[PDB]
Image (cartoon, rainbow, N blue to C red):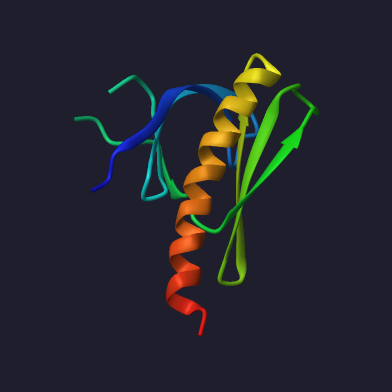
Length: 113
């Protein structure tokens, strides 16, 4: 069954306004990545799958930024996050990567041959 893999505060850059705001995110092993205004009913402000997504690291405009990029149909979705240390970024990117890898292995076992 589906369990939380990692949860915690992330600084998220907005989609339309490119400002940064603190958000409480939860990553689940089915690829669910859900973000709330406060530590959690109250609906989430962000809700997307990390399945088939790409992790990118950047230092501008903020150090220790990571981007989750997902190509969906014609559209490309990007979600931008900042944490205070490069170690915390590695903490998050490793967790997201391992979940994505689990789901990729599952897809490949279904689609290959």
